[PDB]
Length: 311
Ligand SMILES: CN1[C@@H]2CC[C@H]1C[C@@H](OC(=O)[C@H](CO)c1ccccc1)C2
Ligand SMILES: CN1[C@@H]2CC[C@H]1C[C@@H](OC(=O)[C@H](CO)c1ccccc1)C2
Ligand SMILES: C[N+](C)(C)CCO
Ligand SMILES: C[N+](C)(C)CCO
Ligand SMILES: C[N+](C)(C)CCO
Ligand SMILES: C[N+](C)(C)CCO
Ligand SMILES: C[N+](C)(C)CCO
Ligand SMILES: C[N+](C)(C)CCO
Image (cartoon, rainbow, N blue to C red; front, top):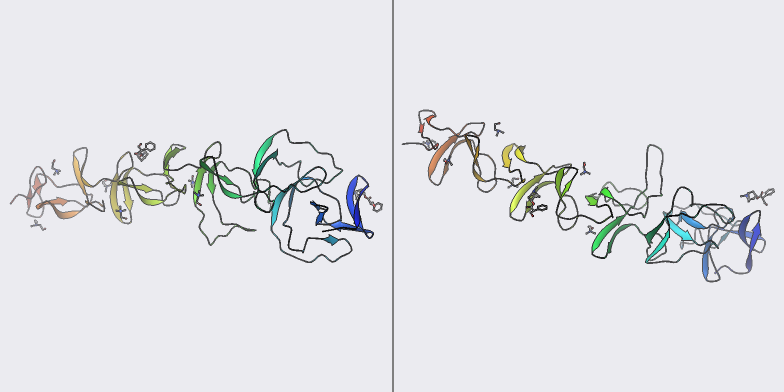
C-alpha cells in the first residue's frame, strides 16, 4: 500500500523514494513486499527480522518517528530483486549460513552450493517446532545457539538431529513449562518406543518424549534414570527399597536366586522383602541383606533347606 514513490539505484544500493524521503523497514509495493532496514537499503536473500504487520515497522519513511517496540524476530527469504518470498508450505532454497544472510541489494555474496527444504508458516516466516511429513515427525529448531554473551539465530528452522529438548519458546526459553527430550535420527526422523543410543536403552513411547522413572511397557515394569533416562538393570535401591531388574531391564517379582542365595521380590510392587514373611501360607525369614535364611535357626526358629519354618 506504499505508492507515489519509486525505486532508486545509488552508491551500489537500492532505495525506494517518495516525496523525497527514503522508505525504511517493511513496505508492500505494487503486489510485492520489501524490507529496507533502518536507513533504506533494500535487503535480499536470507534475513532475520522483526515480524511485519503490526504497523510499528510498516509503511514507514526515514522522516517519520520509529516507535520503540518489542517484536520477535524470524527468518524470511527475499528474492534477488528484493521481493519477499510469500511461501506458506515449503520450498527448496540455498541453505542459510554465516555468509549469505543480512545482505543488501548491491553486495557481493556466494549462492550456497547446498540447498535444503525449508518449511514456512502461514505468515511467510520460516517455520519452527514439530512437523509431520511422509509418516514421520521432524523437529525444526525453535532456538539458535548461545555461549556466554552470544546468540547465533542461524540454527532456527533447521532440521534437528540427535538428542533434542523441546522448550516452550517465544522470544526466550520458558523455564516454567516442561521441556521433554526427544531423539531425531540421522535424517531427522523422531524415534519412538525402545531405542539403543550410545550403548544404553531409552524408551520414547508413542509420543516420542523420553521417559524417566518407573515405566510400565507391554506388561512389565522398567526403570529409566530419573534425570538422564537410560534404562537400569540389576539391583536398584529406589525410594528406600530394593528392586531387582533383569538384564532385559524388566522388574522381577516372586522368588529370585542369585548364585545360591534366594531373595523374594514383592508380588505386585516388586520391592524386596526382609524379616519374616509368608508365601502361600508358609513362613520364611530374610536377613536385612534380603538373603533367605536356610537350614539354620532364626531366633529359636528352625527353617529347613527351602527356608521354610519347620514346626
Ligand atoms: C552502505 N554504503 C552505501 C550507502 C551508505 C554507505 C556509503 C555510501 O553511501 C554514501 O556514502 C552516502 C550517499 O548519499 C553519502 C553520505 C554522506 C556524504 C556522501 C555520501 C554507499
Ligand atoms: C533392553 N530391553 C528393552 C529393549 C529390548 C529389551 C527388552 C525390551 O524390548 C523388547 O522386549 C522388544 C522385543 O522386540 C524390543 C524393542 C526394541 C528393540 C529390541 C527389542 C525392553
Ligand atoms: C509432535 N509430537 C508427537 C511429536 C510430540 C509431542 O508434541
Ligand atoms: C538423554 N540425555 C540427553 C538426556 C541426558 C544425558 O545423555
Ligand atoms: C512401580 N512400582 C510398582 C514398581 C514400584 C513402586 O514405585
Ligand atoms: C512365623 N512366626 C512364628 C515364626 C514368626 C513371626 O511371624
Ligand atoms: C543389593 N543387596 C541388598 C540386595 C544384596 C546384597 O548385596
Ligand atoms: C523358592 N525357594 C526358596 C523357596 C525354594 C527352593 O526352590
